[PDB]
Length: 164
Image (tube, rainbow, N blue to C red; front, side, top):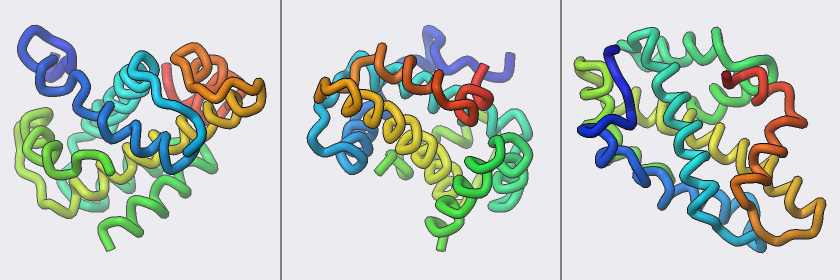
């Protein structure tokens, strides 16, 4: 039990830490669509479940992440994810998260690896939100509810096959 994001100790350190940023993301992907804490908090749970997955492989380089990502993320999302991550090291609290990473694993990490990870995490964030937004805009709703996101990720094998 090396880590549990929502315990009676760590919870305060994560709960709503990504929500503020996600609103921005959902703002760049779908300006017209309105935010909804209920959902973004769920997107957070997912994005956080992703970070944990990228940590099980105990990253120690700015490449080990690319490798892990290159080993997990289903084709096309894997390559696309890296492309972004790379183009980054070259909105999410990249700073406020860096110190946290060291605590999620218990080791040291260069500011370059964090920029890579956080970038990857945000890509899936923008990707998830991007798909959900289309769903919403398809049914003429102008709002992304938690329900929408779920039903949205379903019609997508890549993402659906990515989580469990």
